[PDB]
Length: 153
Image (cartoon, rainbow, N blue to C red; front, side):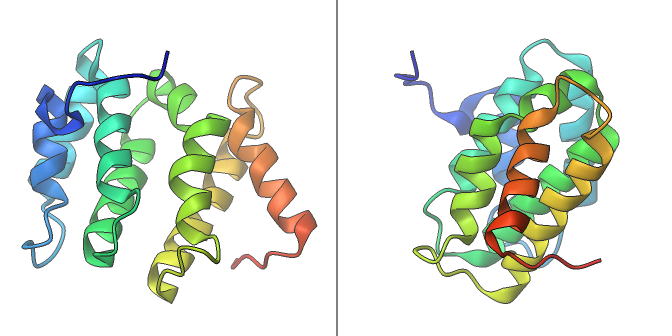
């Protein structure tokens, strides 16, 4: 079931993601962002633990600087981690609940966040189109374009 009670920021990687996306940061902390990639690549629970922490920081957050820092952590992890992580991040539920819901009208984020999310959805769809087990993001990308949403590039 989805009735999970452990705080997403308490796991090993969750502790680093919390610090890497705290609003007191002036800019990205690249040492922490890469340490997060290492934990995802090297440990069994890192991939799923990382997605729960990133989702905690992004969902319902009106501090859009924290949202940006977390989207940068996500961007970094897809570029610097492997298929084990890609299969979890490309899922329909993760992409809909963390990326699409962040840009729906109801949430009304600033342009910098809208553009960051569009770029992630489109870049991931392009990179993952060739893999049959990474379709969730590709389907959402094509559906958003079919509905009228404009993308860059």
